[PDB]
Amino acid sequence: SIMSYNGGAVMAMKGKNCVAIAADRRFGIQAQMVTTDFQKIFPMGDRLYIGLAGLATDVQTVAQRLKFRLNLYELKEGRQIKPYTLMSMVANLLYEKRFGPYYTEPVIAGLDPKTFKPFICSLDLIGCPMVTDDFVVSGTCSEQMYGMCESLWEPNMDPEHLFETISQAMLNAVDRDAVSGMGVIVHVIEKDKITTRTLKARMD
Amino acid sequence: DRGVNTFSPEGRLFQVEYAIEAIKLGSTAIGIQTSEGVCLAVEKRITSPLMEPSSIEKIVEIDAHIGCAMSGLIADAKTLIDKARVETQNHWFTYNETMTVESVTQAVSNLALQFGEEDADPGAMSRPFGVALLFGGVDEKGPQLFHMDPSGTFVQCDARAIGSASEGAQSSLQEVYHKSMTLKEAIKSSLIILKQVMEEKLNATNIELATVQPGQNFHMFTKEELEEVIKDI
Amino acid sequence: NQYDNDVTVWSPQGRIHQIEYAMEAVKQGSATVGLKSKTHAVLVALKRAQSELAAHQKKILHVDNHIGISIAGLTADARLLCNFMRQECLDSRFVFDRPLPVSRLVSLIGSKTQIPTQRYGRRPYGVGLLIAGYDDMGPHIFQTCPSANYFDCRAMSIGARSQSARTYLERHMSEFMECNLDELVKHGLRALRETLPAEQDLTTKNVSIGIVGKDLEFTIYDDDDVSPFLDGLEERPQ
Amino acid sequence: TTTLAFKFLHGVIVAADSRATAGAYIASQTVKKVIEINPYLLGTMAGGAADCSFWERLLARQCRIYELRNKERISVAAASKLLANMVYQYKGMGLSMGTMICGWDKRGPGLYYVDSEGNRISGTAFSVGSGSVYAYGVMDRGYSYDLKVEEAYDLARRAIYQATYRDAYSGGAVNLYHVREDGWIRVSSDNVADLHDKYSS
Amino acid sequence: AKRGYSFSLTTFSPSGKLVQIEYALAAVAGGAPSVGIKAANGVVLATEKKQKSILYDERSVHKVEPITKHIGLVYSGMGPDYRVLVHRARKLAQQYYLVYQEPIPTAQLVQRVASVMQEYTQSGGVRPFGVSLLICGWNEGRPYLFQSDPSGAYFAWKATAMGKNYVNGKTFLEKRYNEDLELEDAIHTAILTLKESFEGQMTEDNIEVGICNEAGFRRLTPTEVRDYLAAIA
Amino acid sequence: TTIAGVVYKDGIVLGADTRATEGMVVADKNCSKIHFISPNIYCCGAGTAADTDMTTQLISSNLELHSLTTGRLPRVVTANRMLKQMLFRYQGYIGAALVLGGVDVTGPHLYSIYPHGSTDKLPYVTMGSGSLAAMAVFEDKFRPDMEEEEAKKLVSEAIAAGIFNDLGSGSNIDLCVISKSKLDFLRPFSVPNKKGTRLGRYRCEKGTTAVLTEKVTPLE
Amino acid sequence: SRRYDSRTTIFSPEGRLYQVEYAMEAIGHAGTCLGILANDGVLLAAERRNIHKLLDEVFFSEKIYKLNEDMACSVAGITSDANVLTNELRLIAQRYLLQYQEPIPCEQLVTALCDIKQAYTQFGGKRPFGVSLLYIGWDKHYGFQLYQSDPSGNYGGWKATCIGNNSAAAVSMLKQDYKEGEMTLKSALALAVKVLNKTMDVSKLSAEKVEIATLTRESGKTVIRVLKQKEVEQLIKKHEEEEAKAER
Amino acid sequence: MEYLIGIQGPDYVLVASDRVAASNIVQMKDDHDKMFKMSEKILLLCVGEAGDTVQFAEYIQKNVQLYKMRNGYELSPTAAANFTRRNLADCLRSRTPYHVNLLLAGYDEHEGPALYYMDYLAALAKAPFAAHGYGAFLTLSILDRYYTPTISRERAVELLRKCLEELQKRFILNLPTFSVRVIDKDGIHNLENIAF
Amino acid sequence: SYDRAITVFSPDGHLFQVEYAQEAVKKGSTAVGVRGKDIVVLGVEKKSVAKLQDERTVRKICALDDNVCMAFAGLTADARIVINRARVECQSHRLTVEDPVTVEYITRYIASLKQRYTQSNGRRPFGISALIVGFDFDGTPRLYQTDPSGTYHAWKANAIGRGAKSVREFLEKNYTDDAIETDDLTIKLVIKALLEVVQSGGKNIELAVMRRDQPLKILNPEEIEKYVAEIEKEKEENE
């Protein structure tokens, strides 16, 4: 499998007035682990984040080319990007390479500027957006992440309760996956603050 | 204002006729064909004594058997000589032999009227080459000398002079040249005609001389080797 | 004065000056005579020299085994048109394995020379050619001009002072058809002699002859090869 | 096919066989495998016969234009790089070559190993071909930097000979070339059958 | 067969002015009067639509043209040149919607349309547009009004006039314009400032008016025009 | 995926499910499969999900450009020809199976468009993974010139048949009713399936996760 | 075809370019635009020409454009041709950020656009861009910087410069009050108002007619802001009372 | 087969590579250098295909030197690592891809010592220690055991020696000589070759 | 694409477009360069810096390679294009040929580039002259100069720009083996040549030196004033 070459897992979750995004930190080729500190979640505008899982090259390439189109959008228009606008921007970027796509599944998590509304979505390799009110997952252990999120998630959750939910949903799903692990980083996005935590995880 | 490919009421292109007028401003060059070989002589025309005399090379080799003297716009000539050097190596690669002097001159003559505005490539020429060339070399038919002009009309010559004082030098070559002369006489004669038409006196660092012969390859006369023929003033 | 800059510009009289200006280029070049019999087609051309110390210009070019030309006007336009004529003859022999008829080739010249006379920035071919060829129909003498219009002729002469040669060929036109190879060449150079002034005449250094027909392929005669044709002349009339 | 080249105190030795095979059948045993690029540069034929002949002749063409433009002789490092760049454009297409470019340079004796794959490495001794493995053995045992001119000939001539004895694709005649400062010279064109009597007696 | 010019027709004068644009601004000045007014509640665009011969079908061709569900256009000057700018504006609005899945902002459309108008002042073998554009729109809870001139520049307006007697219109508008006007009151002043230079009594066939608000852009029916037209609503 | 369309006396009823799967795992429980083309024509989608969205949006963009130039309501045949000529040009590489249906000035027109470019004009069509189950309902209970509420019942039963029998389809039933004067877009028409609410709460207590490093960044 | 050609990319008998020098005349008719360099920051001050009672005012600025996170520019000349050049500057800055993952140095972005403007003066047969630009920014190599661009495609680094209408009189006025090495942003703004007040056509000077933007590095990141209407009026009255204090 | 290893210190970068250029079953070259001088403080360790190694490493090398001449200042180790990644990533889906696994080592005037790991697919990753080849499978475990963030350069070479001795003991391929170079504040320094 | 012919021949047999570019180089600042025994030094004068301008950005001396550097005169916008195209060729030569670029080769490239712009359709000739300075691999000092036409010549001492004829005539009677013997005395010859035309020498002169093994060294105004003071002291000695 092309997606299972580098591994990785990205998760996003909805709360009351807050959005949380979590991803593993392992960078490795097939079986051999290479780097403990690998970035997969990228900032897009103070209160909007994107998590990319799949091929390590395409994770970095899409993030760089999306930032290329993001800054031009924020200079042409005197406003910060909307979550729905970025979703369509990623969908357009991936579909341009229809018959030769980037092997990565983007997950966007963040709050809507000026309207303070939560937003989560995940996309295909060719760019197919889907919006949910609960959770979106992407990676090698997709099935493992679905089993945890379907049992732990609750409708209205505060920032502290949402953090405990997304952390346990990642850790246990990651520990059943061989190609994912070596620490989990969580970004809790609020209207006032961004809380970044690196969780104590298994290093095997 | 008119186009580059415009005919005159007389029956010739303006850009070609103006290119011939450009040669009459350049330095004079004399080439003489002899049974023992072909010699080429040219004035370097040094403007300032600070300039290096070895830098000015109006006689250049195409192959080991062909040399050429140039006059007029020196910048345009270096493009034509470079094309001639490639064509000889392209022929060597394909046929495993050396080209005749007539064949090389004909190859350069193909690039004569390759200029225009409409219906042309983005990297095409706009104006003709304002250069008169004297191709002198030895092949299978013996030592040969050819003259080329902006129009592309190439012809064989026994003795030809082109440059500023070309008309005066041509009449002087008609009175000296004969069929049974030697190469040493051809070198001697060319220097006498050259010193008459030059503005400054003849000197070893002032002029350039080269000979092509059936015996050995194209040779450029060094400062010391010139002294043997310069001493006969 | 205001219409004589481009080929695309028409004169109020109904003329193109640039094509007429290109016709003057053929008159600037030296004279050449082309004539045919019933079995042979002969081209006799006069050579010019820039100086007595320089050799004489090539006036007859080789195109194919059965087709040969004599040029008058611009030298670079002559060789460019000759390369097209050489290629078209090679293309027909490559595909059909047969010699391309002269009537077909001359029509191809009248198609290629027409294009630049109608487009902006482009110029007409400032060269006149006398084409000699032999095929299934016999010997042929064709005349192509700066204008795409071509002529099928019994005998023709074009170039500088070619009027004297044009008048001689008209008075002896009925003799050419039953004329043999040897005498038919003598008729060609005799017309070429009339173009020259009273003092100077034909020599081995300024005369080229191209002969093609049933007996032999197209061959160009130069200096010592032209001497059997010159020896046994009628001499210049006063 | 066995081609070897090594550099020492006095210059560079070029040695090659002459056997060309079309499967099991031998096509020719008089193949000039030492390709004469210039009066100052030499090449070797290994792998593809036409692939070595065409591209090194294109190099021979390119090196002559360099001398006409720059008024100087082309360096061995530049000649090796030019050939490496041209063949690299056709990588993974079907070209097969294993040439060695030898010559005297401004820096001294030069030796380079150029492949159809795109390899370009400078070294003291190389051996290319099907019987190159046997050529490496005998060559390394009797090699020295302070070898005499006559002693350098005996090493390479026998090194090809020992390779032809084991390799089925190697044979014909042992061609030898010496590369000096003024230019290379043709040394010997001894037959394998004639050399068999020399080492036995 | 055709070629195509590659050289610019609009060039800098010795004074330092682009002559072709200066005359393009004179083409719109001699055109039909057109006005646009922003009123916080919505935008109103009105233009003179004189058919003259009565044989003309009024409802066949419209001067007020919609670009999307919330953006419209009004012009002054040449009809044919405006129609190309409508199609281009309609196409650019759709290209934005395919990428971002969001209706195009008014200011963002004008910037893209003005770039096309700039292109024709610098591209080879083309003249500038003889049309000044009035762009209205509703986005982000705010109404917008913009002007795009032949040069390619764009200005944001509260109230502006075009066509013949535009200087008389602009002076009339600044006296008549108020902050926090009502949309229905904005139509009144728009149809009145157009009557300043009209001469031949207004009928519902003589002028065309389009409104833009929170519901979107739409052209007003002749029945709605007739109600506003009889001096009072 | 189960999508269907029917033609009744007044107009057209279109049906679709809400299950979107990645392989053999449900990715989206609530997914819109009835797509907007024009204020009078709607189109159901099947096959490749990304191919269905981008092809629909491009035709909807072209028809909005078309309707504004003409100044009148677009036709179903115009929507059909645009989808027909594009999918044929790509030789079936764009995996988009579309059930097209709308009301024109001519009347109601229904089309079934295949990824290769073949189109069929029928009173009732079914496409997708559970099309076999949906067609069987039509081939048993369909009758010409039926009432609006009767036609809505016919399609809802067809989509439900694909939901319970086919593993590719599930969850909610979406309906789109288009007539000569009325357009009803019923998003959640019927919800036959729901989650059995969790009686055992697995809510993680505050401070059950071990944290190594913490960083707080203030915002405006 | 050649009859209608105006020959834009051609030389003059004197040894100069006509279409460039004619474009240079267009800048001298446009609004006055100046920028000076200080120790703690760098700023741009421009004369707004779009002054009307019925002007809507939607955008943050009229002539000040943002190109990068660390860089900003101003425009003098044709506003139509300016929108093309400023958009191109944003593209080049993002191409560098994609390739090297670092903000583009100030000198490198200016040279990039100057190569394009030089290309239009040499080939293409098209009219050159009649826009002169002033650049302000910060990089890790030199720090705070100020640049000036010409329609010919020529650039230069300045400590204090002006371009537009009355540029010759303004540059000599800047040459008088500027103290090299000891200039702060507080005195920089006071100097900018001093020059604009005397060189402008209409006297008195209002904040609605002028536009000032500042660039200062704060807490490890560059801050680019356009000054408020109330902030400019405060700077004018500080200068207005200073000029009245001269009569003593 | 080729082998690479890089160790980063507090103010230095230590890098080593084998000097073996092998074909089929024979060792052609005994002293092959796999380090490319990018700048005064940047080195490139290129390993992979036969032709892709020399062609790619030199292309980036001359482009970095082009930046130096055009601006006056040199590229930072971070900017050079992102530049060499961009060229490999853009060529990945093209007709001619470069199959090369490289390692970039550099010292910055402001940020300090830096080491970069990069896959043939073009995946850049910052690491305190990294290794390429089949020999990496035997050496990375030793690098996980004895490595400290505050390691001295005399201890780093001793740590490097422990890894190279493992290649003489367990690794099936013969790798006798290794090129050792250190990059610090003064630049690139050549160190004695560890031979067996 | 623009296909119009810009540079064309004239009734008198002259290329005006080339000659007008030669008028553009005359209007440019004065640039002189002399060839010494061990060091080669070039210098520019009459920069017309308003003191309020940064002197780093407006430098006419640019290094093409580690061994090659150049100084120009005329249209400064046209020069930067040529300099950048020359810098790419320096790295392109290194990719094709393992050996570095020689002084003559890079001059040959610039001259051919200027020649192609005088004969191609839709292109305008460069209005610049370049003083190419450097050392060969042998260690022999070299000095070359180009012009809008496309001709290049080697010099011992040459000046280009405004008042170039006045500086050349000064160097025709001063360039001797005694004057170019030491490193310090070669630099003094440059400054003496520039002060002949330039207005009050001091802050107007910008020169750069380069050694046989060491890279280009741009001397600061504090070092120039040291040499200028030494020139006036030797000028004072006689009278």
Image (cartoon, coloured by chain):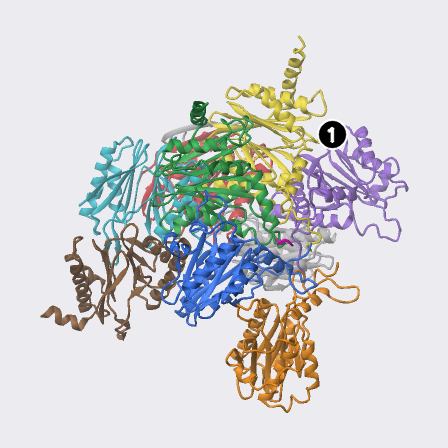
- Residue at screen point 55% across, 85% down: C231
Q: Which chain is green?
A: I
What stretch of residues is rendered in magenta? I8-12
Do we see residue G68 in this rendering?
A: yes
- Which color has been applied to chain A in this rendered view? red
Pick whichever, F75 or H126, lies toward us.
H126
- Which color has been applied to chain C in this rendered view? orange
Magenta-colored segment: predominant secondary structure:
loop
- Which color has been applied to chain D in this rendered view? brown
Q: Residue furthest top?
A: G248
In the image, taking residue I189 as reference, residue F91 lies left or right, namely: right
- Which color has been applied to chain G in this rendered view? yellow
Say which quadrant the C terminus of chain E sits in: top right
Q: The cyan chain is which one?
A: H
In the image, taking residue C189 as reference, residue B89 lies left or right, namely: left
Do we see residue H87 in this rendering?
A: no
G115 over I9 or under it: above or below? above
Say which quadrant the N terminus of chain E sits in: bottom right
Q: Within the magenta stretch, is there residue A28?
A: no
Can you give x and y, in whole percent of width and height, for residue G67 in the image? Answer: 56, 36
Pick whichever, F95 or B6, lies toward us.
B6
Q: The blue chain is which one?
A: B
Q: Which chain is purple?
A: E
What number of labels is visible? 1
Q: Which amino acid does label 1 sit on?
A: His
The image quarter containing residue G198 is top right
Q: Within the magenta stretch, is there residue I10?
A: yes
Instruction: Determine which residue is flagged by label 1.
Output: G52
